């Protein structure tokens, strides 16, 4: 079958070899193994057709690795096609030469690339600038040997800022691939040249020349303000990617501004309406935008501490946006916006997405932890959500009201009078044991605390380690609170824990509780009934040493993941 | 699934025992000028039977089944001592083919109701079945109206077809 | 910084593939749809999937997955915005974007993907300038490809010279079930259709509050532009200086400015409704629709959607003005009023049934979304003041404008 | 297509 | 009211499920508004389209009223589609299926055997135990008849009502007597399945049913000596389905009897020779034969031939027969433990098979193959296999090594050596239930804890992400630090036990989030243990307890408070209650 | 005891489900999607046996449409393959050169061949003639 195609290829008519190579790239389109037809479409490459050679370059790109030995038959044709009156075919051959990653080929590919660097047309110059980074990705030290770094710096020193912007993109790539040996930071005069290059180059070039600014730090108050005054109009651009990198460099450079000067507050108040406006983008950018907002409101919480109405989710929003808007509402929940946030989260447990409702109940809990003012309104709202008696809603609300009781155990003693009836056939062990802590911890305003645990002590030996250990602690606490009624209960739970159970920490805490009860049970009023301190909660603010490293990465995969970059790259 | 012939000299009873294998009957059968074909589902191996008659004009016509041919049955007529020589010459004419080498030989000693019929040993002597290189052969005493020896031949043929326990 | 740009079908095989750096192997795209179903069924559906050290940035078309793979720390919004620009350019080229366009027009699309990106770097992503040297019907590349002004090529000439302005309002609204407004913002977007000759320059005049405060005329009617995000063509340094919208226009249809502001004016169409949810019998939608705006504008072709129970049956609609089609395919109704004037109230009474047996799972309560469209009306009151055509030749173009009030996500929450 | 094939091939 | 196949073509003309659900809900609302008109003519195709929606998985819960109405119809096709919808949309937990009782009962009294066939069909497929108690008086009545189309359905419906109500099987004992000469092999197949079920349920029924052993011996001999049948016949056997069922009833009967096991002796000796290992069916016959031999108390001379059969079944290149031979030797583990042990190289050779199931069965077969002699050489290749496993095999293998080592350990030193090697090479793949088992056996050890805990500390210094490893190690340190750190109350000549990194390794487990917080429970328990086991470096772990008093976990906060009160207030009670924990079994 | 009968295509589309154990519809979708994921992700020299969740599962590839059952893990395993092969011959004899579209368009007849061949999980007719004759007689009633 392929011999017929090679016979069409080995003819001399243009329309035959043209349909032949179109059938080749159509087989390659669905992914047929047309690698065997390599060294004969190599011969049918040097054509006067410009539409045909793009297909051939596509084949050579898709099969450079496939034939590492047969690929030597193209270098003369590349150095010929880089000597053409048409700059489209020259830049086409240059961007073909860069993507071909064969180390046997790229030795002879230095000097025509050097010539196309020194071409007149900016199209082939900005192609060859990216091809320098292509070759540095192939062989970095061959680029260092040829001295293409200085020519890359000379295309920084070029006019017509698209060549300059591709040079800055290539330099950011190569200096990223550097060990920062001979770091290519600029004097501020070339940086002001890039500022003159800013209002002229492409909106993609306006991203990469803002990416060089992630590697430079200004030294003065007037220098930083002077460059940021023209960094500032980039926030009013339609593409969110120019705005995001401008936000990145402004977050980088606002640590140089004098806060006592009125330019810093000018930067603050002019930054927040673009950050609110970026939420109206198309939602795959809104995911990274919400992660970067979380990166900013941890860095500067004063920016969006008055814009709560825009972080309300909508019905059309997907899960990866609705779950992150909850986290931003956590990071921005304050004293005055309590009613809208709590009624908003009240309308979030009414959804069919189970994990969204679980995250919403955890958001109400983190609201009750973060502020002490509306902890009571969180308690009332969560009890009214318990009044729904939806199973996973209760399985989250028990743990959440528990963690409210762990931080603030003070004035919540009439709340547990309802919580005794909370669908006692609850199944999930993370909230069964949570309810065991709620009972035994608050076993002085709960009068029927013994007889409810009789259900919890029946199927005792196969629940968990956590649930059995919470029972083992809560019964000792209950019996210390009432020694009369649960006299048999503490003895039978010590008999179930010590003797027959082989759960090792449950055994150890059982023998400890039994030796405490036998040694001095009155001393448990000071030992296990010791005054618990205020529990240091898990504050999820990212380390400012790591956060300033993540100021330097906004718009990256590390910006999304809220990780250092080396934690996930390979 | 496998194919098989029923050839030989005419009036030997091979179509009589063919419809004895197909239906269990001894039907009125003319001396067969054309051919016959039936199929017998025996031991879940469909023995696809292709009778070709034994008239003088149709003996050279045997080659136009001999393309894509797997087995063979050579039904002899025991009672014809004078025509068993020309049946032997017909057999060795059929066995002198480069194409007929996968066809295992199956000799049906037919009309084993008469005392003038030979045994399954004298027919082997008169044919010389022992000098048959590349020929898995087996002689079998068969009778039409009883049906004895037929399913023994089908048993040995089914042993020849499959190569399993 | 993606090493390989991919487009998959809805099953997961390659519609079209385009590698750039070799950092992502070509066989690693086969894991995408299993990872898609693996993360999707656990609620971890994200635009970034991962297979060990290989990432999967993706946006989703109706039939197409624009998979963008990277291995190192790629610049992410770079990648996603380039995916959106590829979608926009291919929609300009192929007005329907399906597998018939991929598997049959494969002559041009590989050339397009080679031109738009090299080494993972977007270089020239405008549609109209790319038309001029990439055709399916080749000369040197234009200098506008290499120009600083890379959105308007010289040599464009028309007989008449017309500039069409489209001021399109979009009222965003999220009214709670109690009946108060949680968020009343307006995202406004001006789209222009410019048919001029040569290299013109346009200065847009608007009734800005900030610009009139710079002038001293901030006591008349004006618009409070809380934020504006412009096109690339607008010289944004001059707008930062003195609120000046200075731009060489692109040729043809383009969106100039996408502004956003907050508006404490009452909503345009108020939807009050009561729902008598009886067990296993029926439901009732005594919905009323009043208009709070002036008695001179008429809302064209509204579609007031009320989400209904999924297994409802025998639909009944005692309406007053406007037709209803019950849409059970989306589980909703469409109460369509073609001519909806201002200051009027039109009642609709719906009545359904309900099966006697309950369902295994719940259904959810989606808010009410209507689809109004009002011409010759801006709720913000924003008005274009002037548009000065600047040309070395010098002529009189025709700046025409119409005012359109539409919706964005006009949501009102249900009981 | 690949659907018009009979299963057992009798 | 479109046809069923029209909706089939409508859904097959959908590409995207986001559009296919729209096409579902269009015709679904059509069916719903059709059911509001109470139409009994198109109700067949409306319920059929609704069942086509349920088959792909679309909401069809509402259309069960009309399924009951199709059962409450009078035409044959309406009842047919109604019983189809009853078997598909209704089950035990549907809560509305109790209304089928009267309708199936009248259709068990329907004149047609096919409508009674459907009333037996739906009741046998999904008849609830409450419906079994309401219909089994009429199930046996259709067993009190003799219609061979109905007896085969009534027998397996009796199997179903035993399956749902096993205390109702006593009324089918007088109904099953001496119908065991029925010539219809389908009725005979259902009767042998019923006898296999009845013999499976109650031993009181065995004595009534081990009497009719020679009757079914004659039946099986008649079926084996049956050379050919036109129907019932795949691969030259007259009804091998009924042959396997009779051999299975022979397998469960006589398994502890001697008279009946020798009453079935000669037919087993025949069918071990009158089978055929060529196609799948005769290998099935012969494997059920060898199962019947190895499960009854047979002659061991039968078992000589049967182990010869299974040695042939190991030799067969069919992966079917390799699975069968592994399942075979997995069945005859305790029965003939000697002759299976000489298949050991083949059992180990089946570990390198390219199938998950064959590796699993050969792994469990090497596990059950362990005796008090093969513990040395086999465990080396078994742990080599665990090192060369896949993450799905690691839990089962990590459990099976422990279970075969807890029985047949030749040396308690080498026992703990194999256990520690598994705890290194498995890590986070062994089940946490085996962790108190390992704890219980190493505290059943009494003479070697130096060699235990020194090697524990030598291994766990490199790793703590192996979670059950440190689940073991924290309790090991907390109980035997005195044997770990030995005679080192102050600073001496440098021995590798250092009593400052001994606490710091547990503290580093504590600070690291690679901790399931019962890691932290075990670790704080070890910290409170080692205040009396160690007098070397104290009042530094009290610092850890006092700074740990505000941790975020609930029980760990309780644990830190209840420790810190003892470490600051009742130091005289700490050493009083820190005796080692006693040994249970 | 056969606990379930499943018939799923190569693409994963469910063509016939059957439950001889009454487990609810969410569990039906969970178990069905799991089994579809397991069998489609296994090679062609893997004995057609899976030990999945206390079940020696019996599946078989006859075409792109895959067939699946699970006998109780105390019984013989090859006879379940013979059951599926006998039911293949039943569909071939009642339908006639049984296509996929014969199973697609006329699925309810395949359900009824299953009903007249197996109730409760066990074989109720071992004849390959009496069962198809009886379903043609019930069709003759119509
Ligand atoms: N008595 C008796 N006659 C037999 C027996 N077998 C064959 N014959 C006779 O042989 C005759 C042969 O009939 P056919 O079956 O047509 O002979 P053939 O071998 O097929 O010869 P063609 O039809 O020409 O191919 C029959 O009519 C019988 O009379 C036998 O076992 N006993
Ligand atoms: Mg004849």
Image (spheres, coloured by chain):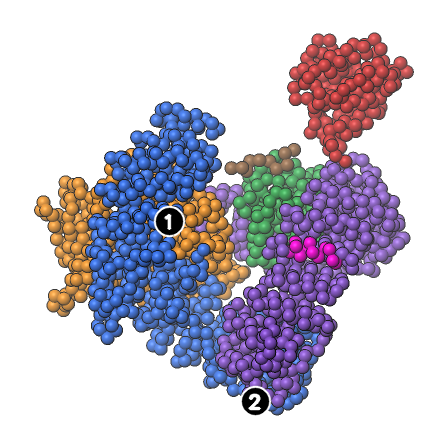
Chain colours: A blue, B red, C orange, D brown, E purple, F green
Q: Foreground: A87 or C258?
A: A87
**Residue closest to the far bottom:** A522
Q: Quadrant of the C terminus of chain E?
A: bottom right
Q: Quadrant of residue F86?
A: top right
Residue in the picture at 76% in, 20% down:
B133
Q: Are marks 1 and 2 on the same chain?
A: no
Q: Residues within 10 Å of mark 1 (few under 14, many from 20)?
A: few
Where's residue C102, x and y in %? 39, 40
On the question of residue B62 being in view, the answer is: yes
Q: Quadrant of residue F100?
A: top right
- Across and down, in percent, residue A535 comes to 48, 80
Where is C46 relative to B140, above or below?
below
Tell me the crowding category of disc 2: few under 14, some 14 to 19, or many 20 or more residues within 10 angstroms, Cα based: few
Residue E520 belongs to magenta span: no
- A349 lies above or below E229: below
What residue is disc 2 on? E569
Whether label 1 touches label 2, CB < 8 Å: no
Instruction: Report in which chain the residue with disc 2 lies.
Output: E
x then y, percent, for residue E229: 77, 36
Q: Nearer the viewer, residue F107 or D1?
A: D1
Name the residue at 77% across, 11% down.
B89
Residue at 49% x, 43% y is: E12
Residue placed under numbered mark 1 in the picture: A141
Magenta-tinted stretch: E375-386
Which-is-in-front pick, marks 1 and 2? 1
For label 1, the SS is: helix
């Amino acid at each position: 079958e392929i011999f017929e195609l090679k016979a069409e290829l080995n003819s001399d008519k243009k329309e035959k070899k043209k349909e032949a190579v179109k059938k080749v790239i159509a087989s390659m389109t669905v992914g047929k193994d047309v690698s065997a037809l390599f060294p004969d479409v190599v011969n049918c490459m040097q054509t006067d057709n410009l539409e045909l050679k793009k297909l051939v370059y596509l084949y050579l790109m898709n099969y450079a690795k496939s034939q590492p030995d047969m690929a030597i038959m193209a270098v003369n044709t590349f150095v010929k096609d880089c000597e053409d009156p048409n700059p489209l075919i020259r830049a086409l051959a240059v961007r073909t030469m860069g993507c071909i990653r064969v180390d046997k080929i790229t030795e002879y590919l230095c000097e025509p690339l050097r010539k196309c660097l020194k071409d007149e047309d900016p199209y082939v110059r900005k192609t060859a600038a990216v091809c320098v980074a292509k070759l540095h990705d192939i062989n970095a030290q061959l680029v260092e040997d040829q001295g293409f770094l200085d020519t890359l710096k000379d295309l920084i020193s070029d006019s017509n800022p698209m060549v300059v912007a591709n040079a800055v993109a290539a330099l950011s790539e190569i200096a990223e691939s550097h060990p920062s040996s001979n770091l290519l930071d600029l004097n501020p005069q070339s940086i002001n040249k890039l500022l003159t290059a800013l209002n002229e180059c492409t909106e993609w070039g306006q991203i990469f020349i803002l990416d060089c600014l992630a590697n430079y730090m200004p030294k003065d108050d007037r220098e930083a303000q002077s460059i940021c005054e023209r960094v500032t109009p980039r926030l009013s651009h339609a593409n969110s990617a120019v705005v995001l990198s401008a936000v990145k460099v402004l977050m980088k450079f606002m640590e140089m501004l004098s806060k006592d000067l009125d330019y810093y507050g000018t930067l603050l108040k002019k930054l927040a309406p673009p950050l609110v406006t970026l939420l109206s983008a198309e939602p795959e950018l809104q995911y990274v935008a919400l992660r970067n907002i979380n990166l900013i409101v941890q860095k500067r919480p004063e920016i969006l501490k008055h814009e709560m109405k825009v972080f309300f989710v909508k019905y059309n929003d997907p899960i990866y946006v609705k779950l992150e808007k909850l986290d931003i509402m956590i990071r921005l929940a304050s004293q005055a916006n309590i009613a809208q946030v709590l009624a908003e989260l009240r309308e979030y447990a009414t959804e069919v997405d189970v994990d969204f409702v679980r995250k919403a109940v955890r958001a109400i809990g983190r609201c009750a932890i973060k502020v002490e003012q509306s902890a009571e309104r969180c308690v009332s709202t969560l009890l009214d959500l318990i009044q729904t008696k939806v199973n996973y809603v209760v399985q989250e609300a028990i743990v959440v009201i528990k963690d409210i009781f762990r931080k603030y155990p003070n004035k919540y003693e009439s709340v547990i009078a309802t919580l005794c009836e909370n669908l006692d056939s609850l199944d999930e062990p993370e909230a069964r044991a949570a309810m065991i802590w709620i009972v035994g911890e608050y076993a002085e305003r709960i009068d029927n605390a013994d007889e409810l645990l009789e259900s919890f002590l029946e199927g005792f030996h196969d629940k968990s380690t956590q649930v059995q250990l919470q029972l083992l602690t809560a019964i000792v606490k209950l019996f210390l609170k009432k020694p009369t009624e649960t006299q048999e209960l503490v003895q039978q739970v010590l008999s179930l824990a010590t003797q027959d159970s082989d759960n090792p920490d449950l055994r150890d805490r059982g023998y400890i509780y039994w030796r405490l009860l036998s040694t001095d049970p009155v001393a448990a009023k000071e030992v296990v009934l010791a005054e618990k301190p205020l529990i240091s909660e898990e504050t999820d603010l990212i380390e400012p040493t790591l956060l300033d490293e993540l100021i330097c990465y906004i718009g990256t995969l590390a910006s999304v993941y809220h990780k250092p970059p080396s934690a996930f790259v390979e | 699934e496998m194919r098989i012939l029923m050839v030989g000299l005419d009036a030997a009873g091979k179509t009589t025992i063919l419809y004895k294998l197909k239906l269990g009957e001894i039907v009125t059968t003319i001396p067969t000028i054309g051919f016959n074909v039936e199929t017998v589902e025996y031991k879940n191996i469909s023995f696809t039977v292709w009778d070709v008659g034994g008239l003088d004009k149709i003996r050279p016509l045997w080659r136009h089944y001999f393309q894509n041919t797997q087995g063979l049955i050579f039904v002899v007529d025991s009672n014809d001592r004078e025509r068993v020589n020309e049946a032997r010459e017909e057999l060795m004419r059929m066995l002198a083919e480069d194409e007929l080498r996968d066809a295992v030989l199956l000799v049906f000693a037919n009309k084993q109701d008469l005392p003038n019929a030979m045994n399954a040993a004298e027919i082997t002597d008169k044919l010389g079945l022992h000098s048959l290189r590349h020929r898995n052969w087996y002689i079998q005493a068969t009778c039409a109206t009883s049906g004895d020896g037929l399913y023994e031949g089908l048993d040995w043929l089914s042993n020849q077809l499959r190569n399993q326990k | 910084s993606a090493s390989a740009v991919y487009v998959l079908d809805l099953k997961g095989k390659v519609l079209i593939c385009r590698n750039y750096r070799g950092d992502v192997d070509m066989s690693e795209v086969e894991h995408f749809m299993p990872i898609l179903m693996e993360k999707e069924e656990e609620g971890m559906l994200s635009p970034i999937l991962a297979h060990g050290g290989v990432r999967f940035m993706w946006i989703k078309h109706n039939n197409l997955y624009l998979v963008a793979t990277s291995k190192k720390n790629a610049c992410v919004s770079l990648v996603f915005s380039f995916l959106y620009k590829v979608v926009q350019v291919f929609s300009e080229y192929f007005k329907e974007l399906e597998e018939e366009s991929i598997r049959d027009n494969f002559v041009i699309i590989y050339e397009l993907l080679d031109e738009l990106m090299d080494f993972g770097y977007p270089q020239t992503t405008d549609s109209k300038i790319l038309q001029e040297y990439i055709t399916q019907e080749a000369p040197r590349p234009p200098a506008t490809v290499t120009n600083a002004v890379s959105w308007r090529s010289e040599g464009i000439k028309y007989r008449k010279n017309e500039v069409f302005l489209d001021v399109i309002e979009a009222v965003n609204l999220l009214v709670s079930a109690n009946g108060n407004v949680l968020r009343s913002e307006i995202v406004g977007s001006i789209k222009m259709r410019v048919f001029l000759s040569g290299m013109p320059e346009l200065r847009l005049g608007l009734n800005d509050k900030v610009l009139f405060d710079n002038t001293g005329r901030g006591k008349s009617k004006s618009v409070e532009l809380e934020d504006v995000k412009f096109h690339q063509c607008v010289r944004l340094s001059r707008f930062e200086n003195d609120r000046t919208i200075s731009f060489i226009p692109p040729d043809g249809e383009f969106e100039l400015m996408s502004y956003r502001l907050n508006t404490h004016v009452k909503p345009l169409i108020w939807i009050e409704s009561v729902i008598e949810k009886h067990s296993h019998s029926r439901i009732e939608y005594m919905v009323k629709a009043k208009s709070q705006f002036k008695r001179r504008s008429t809302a064209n072709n509204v579609e007031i959607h009320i989400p209904v129970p999924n297994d409802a049956d025998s639909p009944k609609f005692k309406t007053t003005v406007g037709s209803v089609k019950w849409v059970p395919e989306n589980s909703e109704i469409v109460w369509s009023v073609k001519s909806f004037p201002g200051g009027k109230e039109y009642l609709m009474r719906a009545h359904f049934g309900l099966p006697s047996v309950e369902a295994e799972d719940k259904e959810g309560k989606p808010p009410i979304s209507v689809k109004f469209e009002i011409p010759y009306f801006t709720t913000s009151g924003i008005q274009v003041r002037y548009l000065k055509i600047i040309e070395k030749s010098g002529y009189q173009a025709l700046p025409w404008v119409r005012y359109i009030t539409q919706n964005g996500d006009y949501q009102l929450r249900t009981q | 297509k690949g659907e018009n094939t009979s299963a057992a091939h009798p | 009211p479109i046809r069923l196949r029209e909706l089939i073509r409508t859904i097959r003309t959908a590409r995207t499920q986001a559009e296919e659900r729209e096409m579902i809900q269009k015709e679904c609302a059509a069916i719903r508004s059709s059911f509001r008109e109470e139409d009994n003519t198109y109700r067949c195709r409306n319920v059929a389209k609704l069942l086509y929606m349920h088959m792909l998985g679309y909401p069809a819960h509402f259309g069960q009223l009309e399924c009951l109405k199709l059962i409450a119809s009078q035409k044959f096709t309406d009842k047919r589609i109604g019983y189809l919808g009853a078997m598909l949309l209704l089950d035990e937990r549907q809560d509305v299926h109790l209304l089928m009782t009267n309708c199936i009962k009248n259709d068990l009294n329907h004149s047609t055997q096919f409508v009674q066939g459907l009333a037996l069909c739906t009741l046998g497929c999904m008849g609830s135990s409450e419906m079994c108690r309401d219909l089994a008086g009429e199930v046996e009545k259709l067993l009190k008849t003799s219609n061979s189309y109905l007896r085969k359905k009534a027998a397996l419906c009796a199997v179903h009502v035993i399956r749902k109500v096993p205390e109702l099987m006593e009324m089918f004992l007088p109904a099953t007597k001496n119908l065991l000469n029925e010539k219809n092999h389908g009725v005979l197949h259902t009767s042998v399945v019923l006898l296999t079920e009845m013999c499976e349920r109650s031993p009181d029924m065995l004595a009534h049913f081990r009497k009719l052993v020679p009757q079914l011996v004659r039946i099986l001999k008649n079926l084996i000596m049956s050379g050919y049948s036109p129907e019932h016949d795949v691969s030259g056997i007259s009804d091998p389905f009924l042959q396997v069922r009779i051999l299975r009833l022979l397998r469960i009967l006589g398994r502890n009897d001697d008279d009946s096991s020798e009453a079935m002796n000669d037919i087993l000796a025949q069918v071990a020779t009158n089978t055929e290992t060529s196609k799948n069916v005769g290998n099935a016959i012969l494997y059920e034969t060898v199962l019947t031999i190895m499960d009854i108390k047979s002659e061991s001379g039968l078992r000589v031939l049967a182990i010869n059969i299974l040695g042939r079944f190991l030799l067969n290149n069919d992966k079917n027969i390799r699975y069968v031979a592994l399942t075979s030797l997995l069945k005859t583990v305790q029965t003939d433990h000697n002759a299976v042990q000489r298949h050991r190289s083949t059992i180990v050779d089946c570990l390198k098979d390219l199938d998950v199931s064959i590796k699993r069965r050969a792994m469990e077969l090497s596990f059950a193959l362990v005796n008090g002699n093969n513990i040395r050489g086999m465990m080396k290749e078994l742990l080599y296999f665990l090192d060369s496993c896949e993450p799905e095999f690691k839990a089962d293998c990590a459990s099976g090594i422990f279970l075969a080592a807890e029985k047949y350990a030749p040396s308690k030193r080498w026992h703990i050596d194999t256990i520690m090697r598994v705890l290194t090479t498995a890590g986070s793949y062994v089940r946490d239930d085996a962790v108190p088992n390992l704890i219980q056996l190493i505290t059943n050890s009494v003479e070697m804890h130096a060699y235990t805990v020194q090697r524990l500390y030598k291994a766990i210094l490199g790793d703590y992400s192996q979670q059950p490893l440190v689940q073991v190690a924290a309790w090991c340190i907390g109980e035997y630090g005195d044997l770990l750190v030995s005679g080192q109350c102050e600073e001496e000549e440098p021995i590798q036990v250092t009593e400052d990194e001994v606490l710091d390794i547990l503290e580093s487990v504590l600070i690291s989030n690679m901790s399931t917080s019962v890691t932290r429970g075990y670790a704080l328990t070890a910290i409170m243990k080692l205040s009396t086991r160690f007098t070397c470096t104290v009042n530094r772990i009290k610092k850890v307890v006092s700074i740990y008093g505000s941790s975020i976990d609930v029980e760990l906060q309780q644990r830190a408070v209840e420790y810190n009160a003892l470490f600051k207030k009742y130091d005289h009670m700490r050493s009083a209650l820190l005796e080692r924990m006693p040994v249970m079994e | 005891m056969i606990h379930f009968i499943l018939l799923f295509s190569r693409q994963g589309k469910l063509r016939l489900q059957k439950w001889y154990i009454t487990l609810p519809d969410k569990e039906r979708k969970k178990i069905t999607r799991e089994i579809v994921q397991i069998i489609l992700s296994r090679g062609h020299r893997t004995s057609s046996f899976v030990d999945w969740k206390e079940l020696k599962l019996v599946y078989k590839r006859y075409a792109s449409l895959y067939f699946c059952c699970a006998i109780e893990n105390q019984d013989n395993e090859l006879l379940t393959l013979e059951i599926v092969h006998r039911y293949v011959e039943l569909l071939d004899k009642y339908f006639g050169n049984v296509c996929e579209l014969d199973i697609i368009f006329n699925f309810e007849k395949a359900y009824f061949i299953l009903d007249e061949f197996i109730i409760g999980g066990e074989i109720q007719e071992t004849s390959k003639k009496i069962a198809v004759k009886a379903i043609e007689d019930s069709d003759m009633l119509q």
